[PDB]
Amino acid sequence: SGFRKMAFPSGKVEGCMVQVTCGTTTLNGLWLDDTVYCPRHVICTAEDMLNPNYEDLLIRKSNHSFLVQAGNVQLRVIGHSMQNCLLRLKVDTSNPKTPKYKFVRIQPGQTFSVLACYNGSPSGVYQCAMRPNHTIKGSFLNGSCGSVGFNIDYDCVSFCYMHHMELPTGVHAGTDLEGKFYGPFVDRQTAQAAGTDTTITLNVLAWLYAAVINGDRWFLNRFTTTLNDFNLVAMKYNYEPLTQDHVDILGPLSAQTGIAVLDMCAALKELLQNGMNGRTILGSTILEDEFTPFDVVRQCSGVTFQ
Amino acid sequence: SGFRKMAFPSGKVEGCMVQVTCGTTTLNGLWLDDTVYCPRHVICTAEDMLNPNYEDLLIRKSNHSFLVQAGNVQLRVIGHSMQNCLLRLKVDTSNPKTPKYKFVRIQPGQTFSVLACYNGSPSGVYQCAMRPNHTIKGSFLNGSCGSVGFNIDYDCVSFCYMHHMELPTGVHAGTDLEGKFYGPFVDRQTAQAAGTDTTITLNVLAWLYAAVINGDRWFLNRFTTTLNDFNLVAMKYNYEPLTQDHVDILGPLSAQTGIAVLDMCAALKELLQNGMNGRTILGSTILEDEFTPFDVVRQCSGVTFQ
Ligand SMILES: CC(C)(C)NC(=O)[C@@H](c1cccnc1)N(C(=O)c1ccco1)c1ccc(C(C)(C)C)cc1
Ligand SMILES: CC(C)(C)NC(=O)[C@@H](c1cccnc1)N(C(=O)c1ccco1)c1ccc(C(C)(C)C)cc1
Image (cartoon, rainbow over all chains, first blue to last red):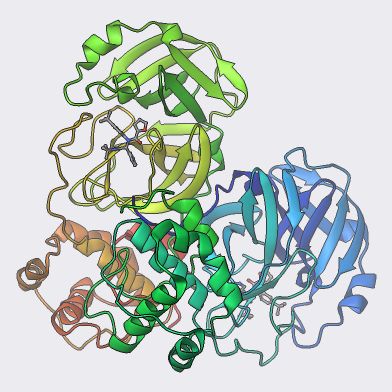
């Protein structure tokens, strides 16, 4: 029993973290086989974060311009290339700790674990969602750049995020491991700001199922709803529209609990319209939206208290 | 910026997890140097969880009664002893992955990271507090026994918890690594239940400081309070009494923010008396009590937005 924001064990990612330094700038790099991945903004001059030309800033560098340290071992750089907003650094040593891995681009609503790192040294691990506005509500300080987000499945690490920058509202922006930003963001100082966000409706529903699995039914009701009538209400409260695809994804949870998806939607529509009336769900007064249906099946019992 | 429930990186603990099997019972063990630690209830017969005599159940076992597996390697047991509610199993191999470590007994209010494990295989990591009633609100399923709680300081792992059982309310009970239970709990099936809990007042205050550090002052007020007048209010709302010792601990945070502890106490007393008035603090409507002052200093900027 219980329900916690749960991250994946971080050991496999920890053995991949390194420090990358160019001139006076230091940040974190990711060392897989004989490549170190890092944010390209490591080569940005302090003089103008405003108008950097990365192609131009990069030709001015050689392999030995880059200092890479894994623990107390220096890694000799023997090649470099830019890929979108990342630098790909060839090194003289393959990481003996390279886990089985993949690079994946996650979609808004999906969750991942973040290993916060400073100076190549892991400091903490927490769970996050990719927000509909393509930011994450991370916890990151100066020098956290190059920290990565990931999921694990049967000892394969799926890397999905590398941290680049903090936005004025204190939320975070970054890229997949191909260096393509999530969202409309760019790796320079502009007036850019996080767009309006919405609540991840699918995740709220997953979490209501978790609460039922764990033994709580207080918020259910005798009603059903059509998908269309639900969306008219849900969108008034800044919830993402629910689609038949989202209804389908919730099939296994629905089957475990015996609660029809549209019946759970009616329950949610009532919670939105009436409030919580004091009362909590899995210890929470706010409707939680950073657990996916997959996260719920993974963490919860397969039985159902019931 | 940001503020997240943050666990310690789990890699060092992951390399210590093993599977321990006695007869039909399997659970997790902790392998440090040439010793494997596990819950003694591994030797409990399925026939009577009600009245087990562990001394009596243990003499009936030899070294080869215990199967220990680290990954796909079998560890030969070459000695065993009981220490309080744990079994200490001598094995033929020292764990080459043993980190620098200590065994500590934590106090109520203190926080730690939990590495949830099943069949010797780590599945997730989350942060918890030791509750005033000596339980933890974990997330644990059948077979999670022997999962450990820990903190890390300068590459030394301080082990503080080993998981033993779930209580009727779905909260969790266990021991320190000397095998002494936290709380009045015993490792057998009885009518035992978690005692009445209270809110960790010191942690709520730490978290209000975090919110100020991160740039938010909305809940502050022009008032101060005496420690005594605060406790009279606080205890009405099921908060632990604040002592001068707790006031002292909050010194560094107070100094970083320029807010007197008793002034923050007045702020909290107002939040308790008036409610939240909608409104959130660091994304939360409930006053959060599972971050210590040490957790705040560790995660937050040392500057102050402010
Ligand atoms: C507010 C802002 C000026 C944008 N700061 C950051 O983005 C922090 C930062 C701070 C906290 C968490 N993550 C990043 N930040 C950094 O911490 C940083 C840069 C290099 C090493 O650490 C940062 C990131 C990118 C830049 C650009 C792309 C403009 C060169 C500059 C600084
Ligand atoms: C509700 C209760 C019957 C007490 N179940 C548990 O404690 C679960 C358990 C379930 C979920 C999380 N943690 C423990 N539980 C177990 O999962 C367990 C026992 C052995 C391997 O896994 C358990 C723990 C202790 C016992 C005693 C001490 C009575 C022999 C029995 C079972």
